[PDB]
Image: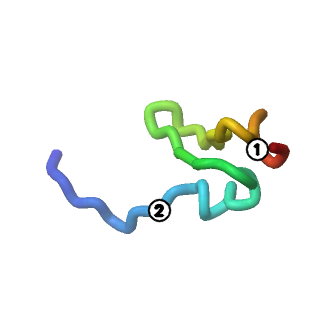
Amino acid sequence: GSSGSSGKKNPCNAEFQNFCIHGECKYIEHLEAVTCKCQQEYFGERCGEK
């Protein structure tokens, strides 16, 4: 239809806030799945270890 962003909010800071310890979080829409990017120092899924 048309635009109309109604209340924008990501699960990265709603429910999965306690997931991405140290890293950039990006909720995937096309896949409806949340992920946690780990920097060079960090690794894994949550990216808690560096």
Residue 47 in picture, x, y percent from top left:
76, 43
Q: Which mark is residue 46?
A: 1
Q: Depth check: 19 or 11 in front? A: 19
Q: Residue at x 67, y 36 (%)?
A: 40
Q: Amino acid at mark 1?
A: Arg
Q: Earlier in the sequence, mark 1 or mark 2?
A: 2
State the residue lying farthest toward the bottom. 7
Left or right position of 13 against 20 = left
- Which residue is tagged 2? 9
Residue 11 in picture, x, y percent from top left:
58, 56
Q: Amino acid at mark 2?
A: Lys
Crowd tier of the residue under label 2, counting other residues whose Cα lies within 10 Å: few below 14, some 14–19, many 20 or above: few
Q: Residue at x 47, y 62 (%)?
A: 9
Q: Secondary structure at mark 2?
A: loop
Q: Secondary structure at mark 1?
A: loop
Left or right position of 6 against 19 = left
Q: Depth check: 42 or 35 in front? A: 42
Q: Residue at x 67, y 40 (%)?
A: 38
Query: What separation in Å lies between label 1 and label 2 (alpha carbons)?
Result: 20 Å
Residue 20 in picture, x, y percent from top left:
70, 51
State the residue lying farthest toward the left. 2
Q: Depth check: 26 or 22 in front? A: 22
Q: Residue at x 32, y 65 (%)?
A: 6
Circle count: 2
Indicate the quadrant where residue 49 lies. Answer: top right
Measured along the vertical axis of the image, is residue 25 above or below residue 17? above
Residue 46 in picture, x, y percent from top left:
76, 44
Crowd tier of the residue under label 1, counting other residues whose Cα lies within 10 Å: few below 14, some 14–19, many 20 or above: some
For the N terminus, give its image quadrant: top left
Q: Depth check: 32 or 38 in front? A: 38
